Length: 537
Ligand SMILES: [Ca+2]
Image (tube, rainbow, N blue to C red; front, top):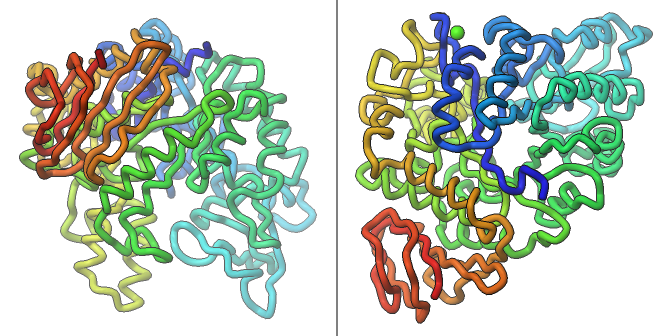
């Protein structure tokens, strides 16, 4: 069985993980210095967000050199040492592959910008104006048009992200091969695989207003697989915001020779108004969350596909703050989310700080925000006459900076992340929420995660068991079996902050709970966020 089926992946956001040299920015030696901790937790691979040379307009996802380490993280020697040291701790390094677009400071674009007959011109996507305006109405994810005018040539170039992230032309065969060759450079270094940034965009065909899920998407990924990682025994996970369960199978079916799995984001729109943006808020309906969770467990054919499982990453807020309670039920709520996900079918991903229940970090004004996405939304909506208080509130609920606050190691200055002012200020709640405190408390969120990881590593039912929904529970209660041959485990979870009834004729032996353990479930009242795992007898 391929190693990643059994694995738990941990995402490190490098700028915010551990400063080791006093500039307020997390770095590679800092990550190296925390490998003992990650081994204690028991994770098998680190997904490392981008550490390549980058002007930082999108905090590293605007890459100016794919094969150089940005000096704010250290050197290639530091990258090699992390790979080697991590391996000694039984941890593989999964690099973030960002090949839909480059920095506008990438040599290819510096060249292409020179003019229509530059050899690199066709590495990007250039179009004449139409009727003295943009070629079409495609929008950037950071507000405004996806088309940026270039004065010297009189053409627009495409960018689905920042102006400074010009989109690469995947129809260009010379460029595809250079990308493959670059991927092989990294693969040859002994990395455990790639997390593939917005990889669903590479079939884009803007002339036909095609963005995600374009015709050439899967043909390109099959070509890519053959040319690069196809025989390598690495994990590839595509970031696919617009994947359905069927599309996820197309990406992950081993007989299609594409990727290992994909990140799907179906649940993200559950708390926004239909037909609008994530900034247009609406309360989450727990029943809808339940349905989405269940859909991805039951409608994926695991004989011909795989599945990733996550709550958090560098682009989305902390799950306990967003959809749960991060105040007096913080510990129970965090444990509930961990339990219900890690007993699901698929490979789990833990975002740095999730394992201690790090929360959102609210701001009072825009000068406390750094992320281009939030700032650009704020400025456009302010100009359009939206209520400024509600804009701040929208950032507090959906802003990506909530995910990017410095990792909280202890109760020292800046939570032990740095001895100087961090690039982005530490969440004031670090005094009570930090790794040192969590390790000292056996009832902490950290030991729940550690235990869930151990259970997965040591029990095939967690890895390969079928998922079967317990029928006819309340909308706010998610309960399900994992079933492997004659063995059957029951997971019962209250998704809500209020008491819920649960009824079952199963006889059980409890394995793990976030409340005192029960010895039956005949007719019970679940406490807020109460969640537990039981062997069914
Ligand atoms: Ca540093």
